[PDB]
Length: 169
Ligand SMILES: *CC(=O)N1[C@@H]2CC[C@H]1CN(c1nc(OC[C@@]34CCCN3C[C@H](F)C4)nc3c(F)c(-c4cc(O)cc5ccc(F)c(C#C)c45)ncc13)C2
Ligand SMILES: Nc1nc2c(ncn2[C@@H]2O[C@H](COP(=O)(O)OP(=O)(O)O)[C@@H](O)[C@H]2O)c(=O)[nH]1
Ligand SMILES: [Mg+2]
Image (tube, rainbow, N blue to C red; front, side, top):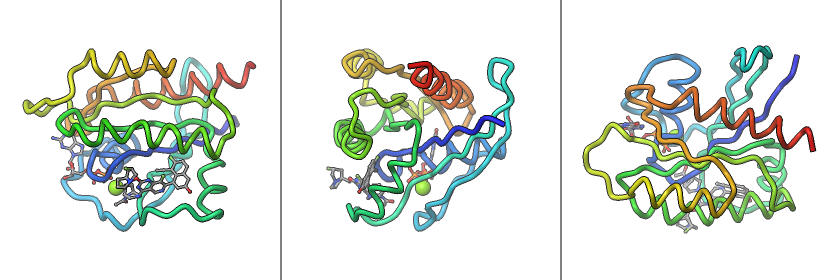
């Protein structure tokens, strides 16, 4: 069975854990332990292919040990998540993309830009801003809500499709 290693990265509080738990459990958590970094497996069918998705939901101290470099280097594609009500989390996307490029030693790593919390009314990052950023990176952009499940399947499945396109060479 085909396995895909997905990694969810981004600032604290953008909804990485809520997105992961929505995908895996079809339920919205109002709180998820900020001390829990972990990987979950989910079997799905994407475009007729039965896959195993291994989803690493990242958390912990900001540290750049060689061990953590190798841990991140195992990821085959990355969801780079910001929240559309938090401009700082959007400005931090550059950082996460650069760190992925660094550990993967490539400018062509499967990535999807995810603007989460799209159910909230207090939007500070406009859609055009995010699509412009994603266009400049050459990656898809998807708006999601872990609360309503809007866009959640599409974000993770689009990442899988990006990994397949990379694997085809
Ligand atoms: C509370 C919590 O769980 N986290 C916080 C944000 C994400 C997690 C882990 N921590 C963390 N933070 C940052 O950047 C935080 C900012 C804001 C304040 C100072 N910095 C720099 C920017 F301004 C943002 N980055 C990381 C981080 F890069 C990694 C990590 C580490 C290594 O060695 C490789 C690597 C490769 C690819 C990656 F995507 C990431 C990531 C993420 C990598 N680990 C934790 C980070 C604080
Ligand atoms: N309204 C709304 N709240 C969300 C959404 N995603 C996450 N949250 C909330 O934002 C807070 C932080 O989410 P969390 O998953 O812990 O973010 P993480 O730090 O990136 O893992 C929690 O209270 C979640 O309930 C969303 O799409 N909409
Ligand atoms: Mg979390």
